[PDB]
Image: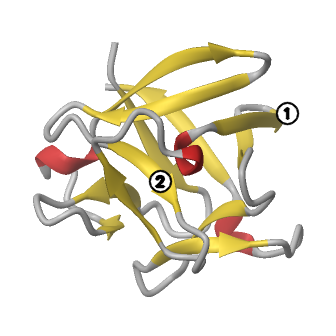
């Protein structure tokens, strides 16, 4: 039950790379864009890469990458639907929203109005 996470603004997909970097791509065939959601309970989820097995992580320095440490505090996310399949993903640890920028970089922000925090989630 894989899902794709897609930018509403640009249509770019959230991708993880073999080196652990996380960014955006327009290549629908990239194997790094398939994710699996697992419940943590209490409204939290993990997002795990089908390709690499790494979980999506946000770090104290604001960077977003992947990790295989299931105990890392930065891998818990909260999906907040806004209606019509639009969602925000908020980090339990930092309080930031996951942001994909038009240039394909992925980081965090507290700006509710940033167009890059708007995500769609669709089955692959």
Q: What's the residue at 47%, 53% (across, down)?
A: 57
Q: Residue 66's x, y, as percent?
A: 33, 54
Mark 1: secondary structure? strand
- Quadrant position of the C terminus in the picture: top left
Q: What's the residue at 49%, 17% (across, down)?
A: 38
Q: Residue 101's x, y, as percent?
A: 54, 79
Disc on the earlier residue, 2 or 1: 2
Foreground residue, 121 or 66?
66
Residue at the bottom extreme of this rendering:
103
Q: Which mark is residue 110?
A: none
Mark 2: secondary structure? strand
Foreground residue, 66 or 89?
66
Left or right side of 6 for 51: left
How many C-alpha atoms fall within 10 Å of the one at disc 2: few (<14), some, or many (≥20)? Answer: many
Q: What's the residue at 35%, 41% (across, down)?
A: 69
Q: What's the residue at 60%, 77% (across, down)?
A: 62
Left or right side of 28 for 91: right
Left or right side of 36 for 122: right
The residue mark sitting in front, 2 or 1, is 2
Disc 1 marks which residue? 83
- Quadrant position of the N terminus in the picture: top left
Cα distance in 3D space between marks 2 and 1: 25 Å
Left or right side of 29 for 40: right
Q: Report which quarter residue 83 is drawn in.
A: top right
Q: Residue 25's x, y, as percent?
A: 29, 66
Q: Residue 36's x, y, as percent?
A: 37, 25
The correct choice, above or below, for 19 with respect to 123 in the image is below
How many C-alpha atoms fall within 10 Å of the one at disc 1: few (<14), some, or many (≥20)? Answer: few
Disc 2 marks which residue? 57
């Amino acid at each position: 039950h894989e899902v794709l996470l897609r930018s509403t603004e640009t249509g770019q997909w959230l991708r993880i790379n073999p080196d652990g970097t996380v960014d955006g791509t327009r290549d629908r065939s990239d194997p790094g864009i398939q994710w699996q959601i697992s419940p943590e309970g209490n409204g939290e989820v993990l997002l795990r890469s089908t390709e690499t097995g790494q979980w999506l992580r946000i770090n104290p320095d604001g960077t977003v990458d992947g990790t295989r440490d299931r105990s890392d505090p930065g891998i818990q996310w909260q999906i907040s639907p806004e209606g019509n399949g639009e969602v925000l993903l908020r980090s339990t640890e930092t309080g930031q929203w996951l942001r994909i920028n038009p240039d394909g970089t992925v980081d965090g922000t507290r700006d509710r109005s940033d167009p890059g925090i708007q995500w769609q989630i669709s089955p692959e």
